[PDB]
Image (spheres, coloured by chain):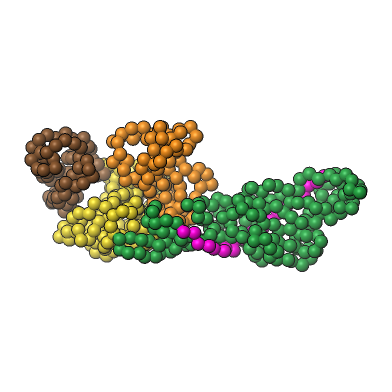
Chain colours: A orange, B yellow, C green, D brown
Amino acid sequence: LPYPQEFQIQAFVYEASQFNVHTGSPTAAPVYFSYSAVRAYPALGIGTSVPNLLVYVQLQGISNLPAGKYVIVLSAVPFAGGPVLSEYPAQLIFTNVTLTQ
Amino acid sequence: TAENFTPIRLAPFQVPAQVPLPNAPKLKYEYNGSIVITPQQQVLKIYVTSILPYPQEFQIQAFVYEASQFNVHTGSPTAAPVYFSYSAVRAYPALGIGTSVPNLLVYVQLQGISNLPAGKYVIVLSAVPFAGGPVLSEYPAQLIFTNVTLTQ
Amino acid sequence: STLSLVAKGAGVVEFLLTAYPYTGNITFAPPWFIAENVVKQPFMTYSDLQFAKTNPSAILSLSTVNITVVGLGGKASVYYNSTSGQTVITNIYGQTVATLSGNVLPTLTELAAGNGTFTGSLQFTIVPNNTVVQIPSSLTKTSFAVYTNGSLAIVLNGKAYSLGPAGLFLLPFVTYTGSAIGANATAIITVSDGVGTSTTQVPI
Amino acid sequence: AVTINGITFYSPVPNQTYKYGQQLVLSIQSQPNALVTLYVYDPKGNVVYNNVYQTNSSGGLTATIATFGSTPGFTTVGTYTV
């Protein structure tokens, strides 16, 4: 279904010891908060863009943050003014991630 | 070969990448017009074209820069440590031939600056393979908007 | 004296907005659902109580004095009240918002002799009411000023009646910092930059 | 060599070790008429060396950038991010 406008995959970085890695929830403060304004492609012209995105979720310190067992909560939250998301998942959590810097 | 190969170029939304204007060098291309943004956040509304099925995805690199810091004698901004970002461009992850998207409207993202200044801006962009990818370009990839204004 | 009553289920609630969407293009509709805290049973206060109070059940008739439509907050109802003789329609504000002469909703009645089960089928559009919700300049630095998500609005015979905020009903909605966000709103985005402050607006 | 983003990084490459009076080199395969505004971010988050260098009309460049050890803010330990 079409979404043409801006939303954001809100990136909140954590360790695996700052994350209870079974319940899908943090047990601490972000160790980085940054956002990725995702101007998602319409479904109104499948030909003019495709509504199945790959997003390179952007963060300003996780190529500046060091190697180690990280966990990131990626939240689909609208940059408000944009249509609805998520008839569910509303998030994707990587719970065994490994940064390398 | 040309089953997959795929030239890919950047051009404005003011003038399509469907066909770009002959003010573009192959070795440069400062667009002599403007990005006209939507001012919600500064968003380089453009087109990109991928022709043939493209099996990997790629990038539309992007960096916000002061116009007080600009060298107009070679088309290269001269400074401004501010914010940088880039877009994913998906067509499809096609398993060979038969899955292509001809026109891709890409509204390039920069956002996450909010403690560093704004002003009258210049922004360089470029159709950018994924890390020395497949062979793009009959040009221009390189898009330097001489007129941008930043909003945080 | 009050005697034996067979009562079991009752009506059926619909969970799509049907027969007139309010989509910006009318052709197209997304998957509306009225929010499903519906505690269940379109409340079945018999027309023929005196019959109830004697004989156990047969084919039994109802003042359709309610149809439960509970959501996140409040409730709304579209109920054929067989003691006024007309379609009483109420909303989450609380009030009777329309009152439509004679039979123009069908009567709920029992489907068998010995039963307690009744039907339900409802048709909606959206007519919005709006209400600003402020969001900080400590996040993206673009202060969002966001109008309330749409407002549910029943239709009978092609005529529309406000059932109230669709951010206390229509799912999926979303929240950014507790701001109801979904169809037929607007955010005035007060874009505060090193240039100053502009103010654009984005329709939802 | 690694072709970071289409421009062929020949130098810097991620992980380079330097000593007293040793040189940072800039050689990258650019598209012509390119500048590189080159920022040596020190471990206190500051550009102790900003300088603007010019690539040549071919695609290439071999430039000497910054002489580390021979200038103040490089005379003692620690990690930079160019």
- Vertical order, C170 against D2 (above or below): below
Q: Nearer the viewer, residue B100 or A34?
A: A34
Q: Main secondary structure of the magenta part?
A: loop
Q: Is residue A13 magenta?
A: no
Q: Quadrant of residue C9?
A: top right
| x 67%, y 60%: residue | C94
User: Residue B139 at x, y = what percent?
Assistant: 26, 54
| x 60%, y 51%: residue | C72
Q: Quadrant of residue B132?
A: top left
| x 39%, y 56%: residue | C137
Q: Is residue C34 left or right of residue B91?
A: right
Q: Is residue C126 visible?
A: yes
Q: Which residues are magenta?
A: C115-134
Which image quadrant: the N terminus of chain D? top left
Q: Nearer the viewer, residue D27 or A60?
A: A60
User: Residue C44 at x, y = what percent?
Assistant: 78, 51
